[PDB]
Amino acid sequence: GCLEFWWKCNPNDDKCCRPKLKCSKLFKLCNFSF
C-alpha cells in the first residue's frame, strides 16, 4: 500500500495502509491488530 508496519504515521495523512495497520498510541507507529 503506502507504508508497512512499524513505519511511523501521522493523524493528518496516515501511513497505515494495511487492513490491520493503524497509527496506534503504543509508540506512534503503524501497529498490528493481533
Image (tube, grey):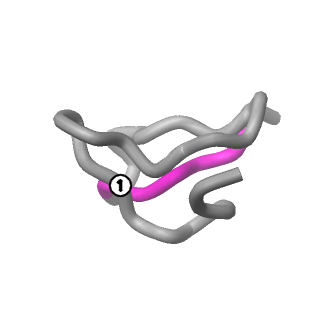
Q: Position of residue 22 (x, y in %)?
A: 53, 36
Provide residue 6's location: percent of width, then percent of height.
56, 68
- As rendered, which of 26 and 23 lies closer to the eye? 23
For this orientation, the residue located farthest to the front is: 1
State the residue position of label 1.
9
Looking at the picture, tell me which residue is in the foreground, 2 or 23.
Answer: 2
- Count the marks: 1
9 to 18, vertically: above or below:
below
Q: Is residue 26 above or below residue 34?
A: below
**Which sits in the foreground, 14 or 30?**
14
Callout 1: few (<14), some (14-19), or many (20+) C-alpha neighbours within 10 Å? many
Residue 29 sits inside the magenta stretch: yes
**Quadrant in which residue 13 is drawn:** top left
Expressed as whole percent of the image width and height from the top left, the position of residue 14 reads 36, 41
Say which amino acid is labelled 1. Answer: Cys
Question: Magenta part of the protein: which range?
Answer: 28-32
- Is residue 9 shown left or right of residue 21? left
Residue 24 horizontal side relative to residue 11, left or right: right
* Residue under the point 50% across and 70% down: 7
Instruction: Quadrant for the C terminus, please.
Output: top right
Local secondary structure at mark 1: loop
**Res 9 quadrant in image:** bottom left
Extreme residue toward the left, this view: 12
The percent position of residue 20, horizontal first and vertical second, equals 75, 32
> Is residue 1 part of the magenta span, yes or no?
no
* Residue at horizontal 18 percent and vertical 35 percent from the top: 12
Residue in the picture at 39% in, 65% down: 8
Q: Main secondary structure of the magenta part?
A: strand
Image vertical order of residue 2 relative to residue 12, above or below? below
Residue at 58% from the left image edge and 49% from the top image edge:
31
